[PDB]
Image (cartoon, rainbow, N blue to C red; front, side, top):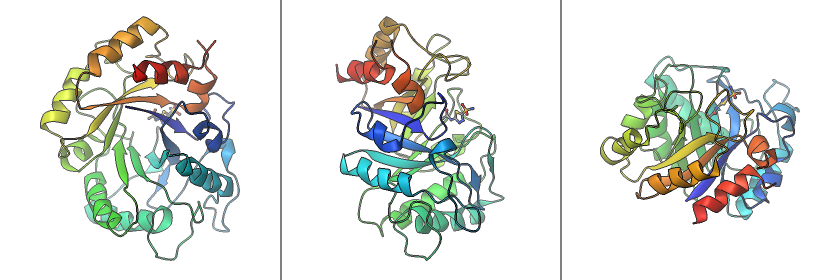
Length: 283
Ligand SMILES: CC(=O)Nc1nnc(S(N)(=O)=O)s1
């Protein structure tokens, strides 16, 4: 089991470099937040990158260096598409399939000469954090990416970030119709959070019975601090322990995901929140 953390949007204000969190040993998977504009490419990583190519697209040499450092240390670094707010849509499947090629050539191991925000660094795949209630294109995009990944020289990963209500109005189709490695389910800002009417059991049925990938790994997505989300933050370590005990008893359990790194690393409970969770997973 693994800890995934979103990084890039500086929820806490005190966000450190990506490599700083990779070097902490409290997290395993890093989701760069976000490619918030597409098909016409646009990235945003708050204070962590501000230089651009002449045409306005972010050019991020420090993030590039840090992606490589993270990977050397055994971490997986995915590019997260979308995010709450932000400016994106596919008109249809054909447009989304074209966009698979664009992602491969821009961020992956594709050889098509185009501007690369991370220079020679190569992401380990993509997270679909679609939050606009429009599901067009993503299944097609995911499926096309899988075909392109065969050209690469390492394993690539695709993940999605549904909110806990099932089915998810943005990535539900993606999750039902494409092969997905990880579902980082947001158990926050919603009725189905851990202290609400927690609906892990529904997500488990989805994993065993609906997901094209029967080996999909489901993650308990949580806010990293009281200030990381409106509702859903858990500070009761007993509840965390028992929650983990309940859900870790299947092969479908992948670990915990956190919004976001700046929050989970700085929020102390006098030990970082991310450390508390990493440690509960280990047992
Ligand atoms: C997976 C996830 O939590 N994604 C988010 N995107 N934007 C967020 S926001 N409203 O806190 O800035 S959270």
